[PDB]
Amino acid sequence: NESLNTGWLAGLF
Amino acid sequence: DVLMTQTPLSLPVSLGDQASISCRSSQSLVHSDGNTYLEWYLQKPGQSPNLLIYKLSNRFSGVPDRFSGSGSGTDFTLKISRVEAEDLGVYYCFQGSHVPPTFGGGTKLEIKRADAAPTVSIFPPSSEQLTSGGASVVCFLNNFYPKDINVKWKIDGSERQNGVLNSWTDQDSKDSTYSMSSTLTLTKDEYERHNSYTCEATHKTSTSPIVKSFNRN
Amino acid sequence: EVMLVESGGDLVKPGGSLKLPCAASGFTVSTYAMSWIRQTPEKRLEWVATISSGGSYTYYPDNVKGRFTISRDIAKNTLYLQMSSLRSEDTAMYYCARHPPTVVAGDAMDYWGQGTSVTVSSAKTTPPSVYPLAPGSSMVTLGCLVKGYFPEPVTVTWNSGSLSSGVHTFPAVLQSDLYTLSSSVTVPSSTWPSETVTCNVAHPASSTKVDKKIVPR
């Protein structure tokens, strides 16, 4: 559920 | 912050044609994972933006057909074949690769249509306004195409720029024409110094200007 | 379908505070990554904040960092934006947006709300003055000048709405922290003055409603 955004969004955290 | 530089902010294009909006990035937007997080959005008038393309060359669900994301590295091209009425609005490119994520300034997709000469109306101030101590002279220039127009005020045969305010509509979504208001605002006293007021428009539809005026009497 | 409805927008003094909510219907907030994005009066879109799909992480670009807080309330199925220590540069439209899984739309934003409008200013709120625009001398054109109100927005109708063909309402112009707009209307000259045309103006913020018959001078 913190696994749906791999790809660029992950970058924001 | 990666500069997303896009903006021919127009391209003039007739229905059923090709259309190519470009977007240039500050640097390469190729992610450390060998992806390109470049996105395309369309904002139709009076709406939020809509997703068109993500990841450089990926069309989103339901997003038509004629929409296509091409490009690589620093240069990108959204490319609309066909061009329907529904495509009107402002296209933004967007970068997700670099850590303050950034937008382009948008390109408006201008729809070509038959040339129309403006309809010029000029209005002396209201008497109610005069009682309050001001006097606004208003000039409407309506339903013309193309967008390129010159408005010019004249007071007793003499040009004037100071104290002129202008407002332009976005392309009308129904008949794709443009329109514009122009106001000269003066104090009652100031206004009453001069007799004749003129509002003259220069548009590609006419080699000589369109003139509307009046007198105080 | 999926729907996000921002609310909470308002006029506030610089250095002030306020909270936007954004209510989701059509999907659960607790299963999506969500951002606030703003669009300035000049149509420039800039990033405001983001919360992780699982709700454990937050991002803010440097210009809003430390002043702003994005929260979510999974029970209310609502996203929040607490905005403190406000600057006039923060004046813009605040959109609320979701990101589907990276498998769906490469971390792009599929749905955007409709915006709430925030204005950071100390300028005092002021009802408008409304003036007829009748000509002084086939298709007769008329107008309303709506002068000296703040803040936005203002709503202009003609014969309580019954009249919509041939209407243009120009974007407001801001001089001296007060706004001014005008609306045009067209009508066959035969229906004048057989049918008394009235423009109706409302300025919610100041509880102002003014109807205003246009009569011919």
Image (cartoon, coloured by chain):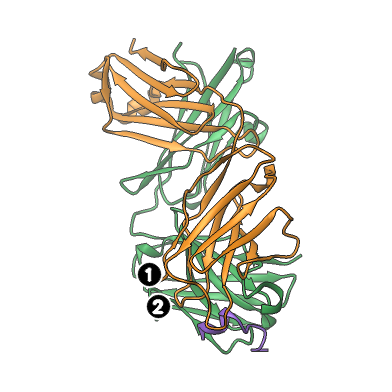
Chain colours: A purple, B orange, C green
In this figure, which residue is indicated by the disc labeled 1? Answer: C86
Q: Is residue A3 left or right of residue B27?
A: right
Camera-side residue of B49 and B203: B203
Q: Residues within 10 Å of mark 1 (few under 14, many from 20)?
A: many
Residue C127 sits in which quadrant? top left
The answer to whether residue C45 is left or right of residue C198 is left
In the rendering, at what x and y percent does residue C85 appear?
Answer: 36, 73
Query: Is the N terminus of chain C in the top left, top right, bottom left or bottom right quadrant?
Result: bottom right
Residues at discs 2 and 1 both on one chain:
yes
Image height of B63 relative to B118, above or below: below
Per the image, the residue denoted by label 2 is C67
**10 Å neighbourhood of mark 2: few (<14), some, or many (≥20)?**
some
Q: Amino acid at mark 2?
A: Arg
Number of dots carrying numbers = 2
Residue B55, quarter of the rendered image: bottom right
Instruction: Give the chain letter at badge 1.
Output: C
Q: Earlier in the sequence, mark 2 or mark 1?
A: 2
Pick whichever, B185 or C34, lies toward us: C34
Is residue B45 at all visible to an observer of this figure?
Answer: no
Above or below: residue C121 compared with residue B139: below
Disc sitting over residue C135 in the figure: none
Front-most of residues B112 and B88? B112
**In-front residue for pair C124/B44:** B44
Quadrant location, the C terminus of chain C? top left
Chain on which label 2 sits: C
Indicate the amino acid at tag 1.
Answer: Leu
- The location of residue B140, given as percent across then percent down, is 46, 26
State how far apart marks 2 and 1 are (Cα): 8 Å
Q: Secondary structure at mark 1?
A: loop
Q: Are marks 2 and 1 in contact (CB under 8 Å)?
A: yes
